Image (cartoon, rainbow, N blue to C red; front, top):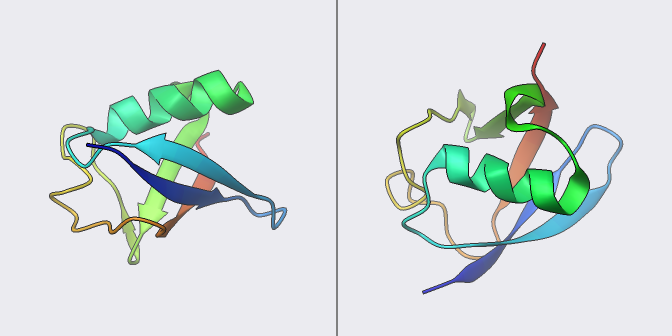
Length: 75
């Protein structure tokens, strides 16, 4: 299945993103690249005070539809 979540950047700008619970964090990064043009290696995704790990899924992190990730520039 699919759901909508949100990604909020430090500018305050918040964007919809269409994901699946089975998506790995790297796949979610891949979606942000298509929509916004940010390569995955310029991205960190934070939720619940943690940096989310590649190889884990949204379902593993218990991230609910209409939740909000923070998007952070990886340096």
